[PDB]
Length: 539
Ligand SMILES: O=c1ccn([C@@H]2O[C@H](COP(=O)(O)OP(=O)(O)O[C@H]3O[C@H](CO)[C@@H](O)[C@H](O)[C@H]3O)[C@@H](O)[C@H]2O)c(=O)[nH]1
Ligand SMILES: [Ca+2]
Image (tube, rainbow, N blue to C red; front, side, top):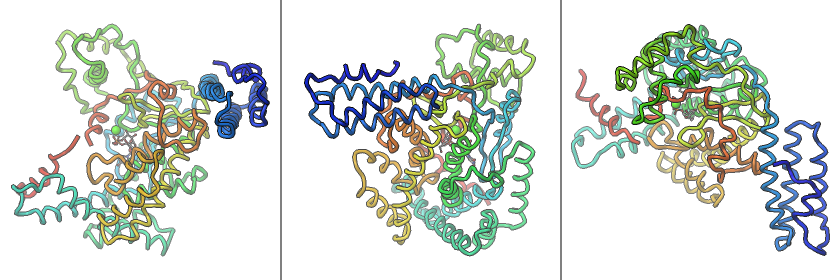
């Protein structure tokens, strides 16, 4: 998998009596100087490969009928193989920072109890729980707007509870039409304030607004902020509102968009995570991930043949939490189904184990190439609940670029749509019709998936988020990397190519109680029934 020589490339692409064309010369020259760059940085070696790839399709575009074309197409696959070789031979241990993010409200003790498992076993890592000291009321504002929209939708459904078919479908449709209004009433208010005084703090705009419109208690809100601040402070809280240079001015604008306007804490955390990884380097994790388990802790408890690999992984953590009680409250539902005998095999293993570092596996030295961002996989697909990146790695810039290029398209089309439109449905139509008119084979899927942006968090099955700041931007980045592009939106990467970027398996346990709980954010008819219930179950 060593890249072909200029010499050998001449053999591949040889056509008897054919003139050495200027564009073919360029290729050969470039490839020769690549083999002359051993002392160069890996990024500089990658950029030399990239250049060569651009020279090759410029030949293939200039001479569409050339006899060289078949080998030149092969050659381009070797360039891509070559990226992998660079990446595998440039491994170096990540900055030992461990990142979590909790924004928009008070951290739960659940979050704290998981994080602690990581902190307790990674003493050589700096744990940093990123929070936004200006934005503790985001979940409150949201819960309030959503609460108000709900109770207004039910008032309108009041006598029609039993028939014909005012079901969950129509509830969310109509509630959404109301949420949009209330959300746009706040955004317009927040915007006006920010044009008035730009030193104005988010939470201060939100309390002023809750107090007037939703009759929310100023005192209580200030109290709430004080508790949030104090709690994260005590728990390695790192305020993003101190940190200077990390700030891409466009990413900052996207973060705020997702935080203050869209109230989507997941999206802003998507944006925040990669930005901090680019600025700080390290391992990023969602607060619902726990450390991996020592390989040997359980290595002689043979899995009963009937139970799945997934359950078993889930069982092992529950065994850990039954017998060590590290996280109080942690479930044993699955564990307690096993034969008493196996349960005791688990108990035994956990008896001769003194400290937590003999139970979980410490990150220690994780290596990564400047060319990559490692990512977790769930169910054969990438998932960005766990990431690894050197500071200022080439792949974190590909990711950030992807986020910027996607949002530009979203914003360029959605802002004009919001402006013109009496209501939600009117705006959505304007927006879809806008998205349709610039859509093509390449970006069609993307357009489809971000069409429902305005419903994210407010209705089920929306996927906009995935395609702007989540898993899609990473496969977009990985394809950019391997295919020497800067615009991948139509992804032809397969699982085993993408496995080249997998977060090391033994060093994370994804199958925690909280995670599995968060995989049920399928459909809830049960909510429109519980909101129904909140109207005969009361005063
Ligand atoms: O009030 C909140 C809620 C979420 N988060 C952040 O979002 C992360 C993911 O939250 P989670 O409850 O796990 O939501 P999911 O929908 O299960 O998250 C999935 O989808 C998101 C895509 O936006 C990604 O951020 C996650 O990595 C991915 O696991 C958390 O760790 C937090 O950093 C907050 O900061 N505040
Ligand atoms: Ca989750």
